[PDB]
Length: 41
Length: 44
Image (tube, rainbow over all chains, first blue to last red; front, top):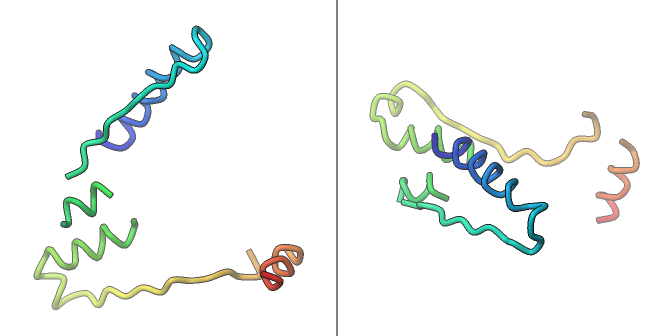
């Protein structure tokens, strides 16, 4: 639900605006929460 | 990253402390599973 879901989400959301307008560069924020920080890293 | 899961589980659970001896070796490169790669890295 974290890794694969958001990675395919980035893929899908970046696919749509690819051929329509070039240099339209998508932006993603990543929620990163020591051991929890290690998992986030 | 694969370490950070199992070793973190080791540090987390106190049952694995007396049941498992977690160990690891950072393996390098092998010449089997070619000669050009070995020559390039031996030049490196």
